[PDB]
Amino acid sequence: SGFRKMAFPSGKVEGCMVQVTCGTTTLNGLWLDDVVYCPRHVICTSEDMLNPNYEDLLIRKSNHNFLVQAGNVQLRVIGHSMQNCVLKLKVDTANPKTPKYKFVRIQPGQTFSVLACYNGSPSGVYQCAMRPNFTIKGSFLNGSCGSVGFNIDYDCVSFCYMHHMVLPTGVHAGTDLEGNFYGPFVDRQTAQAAGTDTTITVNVLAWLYAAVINGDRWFLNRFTTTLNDFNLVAMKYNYEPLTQDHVDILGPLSAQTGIAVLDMCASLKELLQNGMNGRTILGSALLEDEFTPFDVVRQCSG
Amino acid sequence: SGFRKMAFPSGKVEGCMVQVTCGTTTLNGLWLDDVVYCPRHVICTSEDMLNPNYEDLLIRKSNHNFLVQAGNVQLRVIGHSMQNCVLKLKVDTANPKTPKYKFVRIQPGQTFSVLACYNGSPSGVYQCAMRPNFTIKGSFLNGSCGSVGFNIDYDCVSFCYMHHMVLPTGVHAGTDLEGNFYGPFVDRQTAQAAGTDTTITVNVLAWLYAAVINGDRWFLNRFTTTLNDFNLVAMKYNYEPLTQDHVDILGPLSAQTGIAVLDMCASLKELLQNGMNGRTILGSALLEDEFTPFDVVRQCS
Ligand SMILES: Cn1cnc(Cn2c(=O)nc(Nc3cc4cn(C)nc4cc3Cl)n(Cc3cc(F)c(F)cc3F)c2=O)n1
Ligand SMILES: Cn1cnc(Cn2c(=O)nc(Nc3cc4cn(C)nc4cc3Cl)n(Cc3cc(F)c(F)cc3F)c2=O)n1
View (cartoon, rainbow over the protein chains, first blue to last red):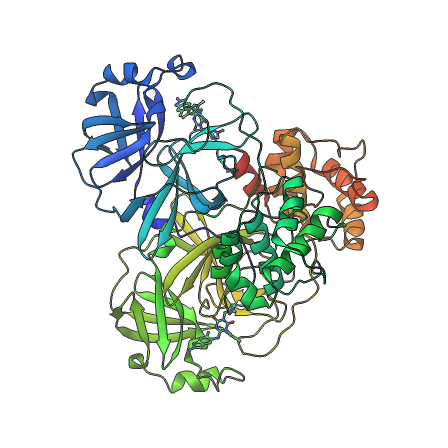
């Protein structure tokens, strides 16, 4: 009963957050075993941030230039290296709270939980989606650099995102935990635009199924459509194309509600062409695209 | 809008969640120090759930009838008592993960984080608001009974909600941690309708202040009002009247923006009487009512 943007419980990740400082530059790091992972931007002074040559900057650093604080306890740095845009500080102490974990690179349209942190201290948790243009529409303030995104399966934390920067439009850009940006961005303090964003079609369909499961059918209709004719209209409205794989992934929701995927597509086509006429769906005046089919299944199965 | 529902980090509460079972009836409990708190509904068999006699059901129970588990580890029950609709099970082990904590009873409009739990295992976290009709629009499945809602202020967890039941409209009802229901609900498996809901005026005002902070201020008018005049008008539009405490919690936002609370009330009154005429506020044609003044200060600062 009900449907809400829901994040994973953050406790396994809270025990991994630390603060990293180089000179006066400071941000958040992630302490797993005897390594702290953080954005390499921490090595920049305010002057360096505008145009950093990171290999040149890092070679001039010593271990003692890195102050790592876990709560109030300082962790001694005994080695350091850089993997793409992630700095890896080897410390002399293993984190006793290290969960089972994996580093993964997520696909556009997939969701994850973000633990927003400031000065190494967790502040809030929420769910986000990787946009098709590889930005995220997060909620982050100054000092959030190094906050991480993750999913939890059983007791295994799959880390997928490390926050780096806010773009001029107010959307956010970051890397995987191997230090590779999602999207065409670079870790430099210069104005950066993203590519044109598009709407995650398979997610909108999942959310319409969530609405039906929760008792609202006002937007359904008796029209049906082929996959190709739906995709023609979707693309006209800057929606991502729907693949047969997406149709299959929606199968369980179609089975549960008795609404064929292509019948839901005909509903979405009418919503795009007619608008919502001031009505709402699951309390929203806009078509929501940040719930995956699995997000819906886990909250509405039964 | 840039604003979104953000939950508190849940780790401090995850370490307190346990499972409580009586026979086959099972739900979640909250382990603080050497006491486990859970809905007393756990003492009902399937046939007792419709019309339970809790005093009779409890006198027939002994300590050894309660199965309390942290994961698969059993915590021995050494005492039991009932406080309103909450059972308190004294256990032989003090929880080493107990945070600094308080039990509080919140007002409608206040928000809190829910840690949804199943079989004593935390599953997800989300923010909710207490509606004026004393329900929450949560997301809960079977097995969620006993999940808790909370706020965290400076290492201290203030527990404010314990989930009991789903109502016919799919909204949710529960108690404070002293076992007193929010609203006119009782802990029995009967259909209980929620009353008509209203819009949380203090939170809409907070949302308008958030818009002003972000430079979206077209709706500010040249008028002011009295609190009494505004309250009488607001109720005609299914909005809650403001209390003196509401005026005071808007203090910081009023000082930050330089917009007097009563001036903002007059601006809101014009939106109610005239609509928004095709414009938006924070990119939305809907006035959001589930962000408190504290939530706005938290996401903006
Ligand atoms: C509003 N907002 C939303 N997300 C963010 C993230 N973010 C950040 O927290 N900090 C950044 N610059 C820093 C300044 C510092 C000043 N001191 C004393 N220490 C500092 C540390 C940092 Cl990281 N930035 C900007 C930014 C960060 C990068 F990692 C990058 F590659 C380019 C950038 F322009 C930032 O966006 N703020
Ligand atoms: C869909 N949904 C949304 N919220 C809820 C919460 N909820 C719940 O999890 N369980 C309930 N009844 C139980 C049945 C059991 C079967 N076994 C084997 N064990 C059980 C334990 C419980 Cl608690 N209920 C119903 C309910 C629970 C109460 F505490 C109450 F006072 C009245 C009620 F009608 C329930 O709503 N489900």
